[PDB]
Amino acid sequence: GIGQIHFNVETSRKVCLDLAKSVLRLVPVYPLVSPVKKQHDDYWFVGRLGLD
Amino acid sequence: ATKAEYALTKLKLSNESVTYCTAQYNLSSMLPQQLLMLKNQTTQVAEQTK
Amino acid sequence: ATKAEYALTKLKLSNESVTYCTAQYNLSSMLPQQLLMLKNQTTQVAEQTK
Amino acid sequence: GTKDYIFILDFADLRTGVAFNGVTINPRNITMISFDCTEAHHGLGKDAYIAAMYNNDDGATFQMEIGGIHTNAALAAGDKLQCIWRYLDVNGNAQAAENEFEVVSYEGFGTSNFSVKCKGMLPGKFIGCDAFYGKYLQTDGPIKQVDS
Amino acid sequence: SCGAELEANALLTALVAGEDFTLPDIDMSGSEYDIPGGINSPIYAEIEKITTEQLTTREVGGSGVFDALMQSASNHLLAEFKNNRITGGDYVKAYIATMEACMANAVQFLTTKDQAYWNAVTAQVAAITARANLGIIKANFVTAKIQAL
Amino acid sequence: SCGAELEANALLTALVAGEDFTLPDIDMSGSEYDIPGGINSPIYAEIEKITTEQLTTREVGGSGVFDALMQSASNHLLAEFKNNRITGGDYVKAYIATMEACMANAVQFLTTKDQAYWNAVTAQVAAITARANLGIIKANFVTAKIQAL
């Protein structure tokens, strides 16, 4: 019927690589930061009454 | 397959109608002309005898 | 094998349609011209008698 | 998209499963009926999702990511996770299945993304996941206090 | 083309006019036409061979038909005995008396119970297949009328 | 080529339109249509012939139906005997009294138990084949309707 209107698989992978490279170019480093910065062994599980 | 044979029978109906129409045309409009041709040929035979 | 007979019946449908079309063309466009030819032949027979 | 729903417990047709495909409880002997009430943040609860799953060259284990998780969460060996995932059969047709997996180890505490090594074999190539259950873990973790 | 299909449709509509032929509308995937349980129904569990240890395990405790039949009678007699209604001798004599009827019934219960169940799953399957056969009968009614015509 | 196949497809699409014929969608490899066990099921185990050594081994110990039936009764009587309720004479008398019903029931249990099991495997297989026959019936419904047309 209709023919040659959609990409192949390989071209889709190539376009996805191009998009990934562009997005990495905009944002070279990981922006997000986490309050917990160490492994579970370092932290000490304690319970407190209400703050102050 | 039983589904397909139904469509075959319907198309056979479609051809049967045309067979009827052709037979009716041949009866109504073609045979009398052949009869007239025979009536014309007999007199020519008589003239040949003369 | 039962799978293949189904395709055979479908192709038979395809041929039946063309049979109908040919019969319709024959009825609509070929017979009246033959009738005209026969009408032309009868008068020639009469002229031969003359 | 609605806020007017009812919960109906019918003691005929009790089918035990995430997708109601399992053994049926016998109604003629029941000792107690306890509703399981938890919070949204109970054990990496609300926002977890599977992402990828694949086999390993080892005889036993296979690898599984866990996706978005609140920071105050951890997994110990022996924890069980349930999910409803879709895979590609050998013949090339998509299927659906539900399963329960144990864990042996994991990596990535505090970074909100885990990659967990789990026991068992996978019947096919991963496609997607529709439901995930990460409740009842062993290790404690603090959360912001909530009254409800 | 010349529309042979249109001619066939018109001829079929005109020729059989004056009568009603409506086919049945049963939907046969509605879970009323399936055996109740999936793979997890007790139909698909493995059948174990009957052995002597399933009759009696040679212990007063239980885990056998004869042992359970004796223990229930002993429990009933002891229940009457704890109320000051009989003594030890009456309980012992009644126990010894029943000791044989317990065996006689235990030998029969196993053989009859292993069949009383399997005579019911076949009835289930028969009824569920009979629903579909009834649907096919409803379908055959119309063909009967058309054969008449 | 002139597209004969296209003409045939269009002709069926036009001629049979106005009716719904949807075939059933059963998948018949889902393990609900297979006998439960593999080679490891007891169906494929060797059958042992019945011999008199299975009835009684001529020993007080066991390994026979009659011997086990006697030992269980002896154990029950001795359990009542260790409690201060009967003496040795009463125990011996009851033992000797039961020693005939034990034989009478042991002669029957073997012959009935050899059938109690094999009357269930056939029922399992009958149900599992009934599922597939039900599937074929669901498939025949549509043929019935098309035959009517």
Image: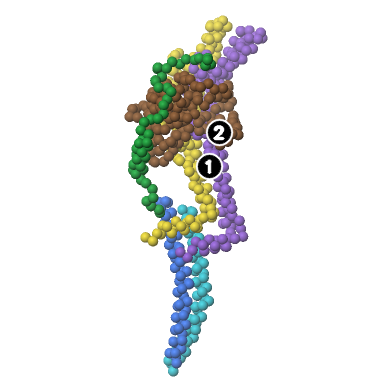
Chain colours: A green, B cyan, C blue, D brown, E purple, F yellow
**Residue at image coords 42%, 22%:** A36
Mark sitting earlier along the chain (1/2): 1
Q: Amino acid at mark 2?
A: Ala
Quadrant in the picture for the N terminus of chain D: top right
Q: Please name whichever residue, D34 or F101, is drawn nearer the observer in this view of the structure.
A: D34
Residue furthest to the left: D57
**Residue at image coords 41%, 19%:** A40
Q: Amino acid at mark 1?
A: Ser
Q: Judge from the rendering whether residue D95 lies leftward or rightward of residue E69; answer left or right.
A: left
Q: Please name whichever residue, B44 or F43, is drawn nearer the observer in this view of the structure.
A: B44
Element class at badge 1 = loop
Q: Which residue is mark 2?
A: E120
Figure check: F48 above or below B26: above
Q: Position of residue A38 (x, y in %)?
A: 39, 20
Q: Please name whichever residue, F51 or B10, is drawn nearer the observer in this view of the structure.
A: B10
Subunit that carries the residue with mark 1: E
Q: Position of residue E24 (x, y in %)?
A: 58, 49
Q: Position of residue A51 (x, y in %)?
A: 52, 16
Q: Residue E29 bears which disc, if any?
A: 1
Element class at badge 2 = helix
Q: Nearer the viewer, mark 1 or mark 2?
A: 1
Q: Position of residue E30 (x, y in %)?
A: 55, 41
Figure check: D35 above or below A22: above
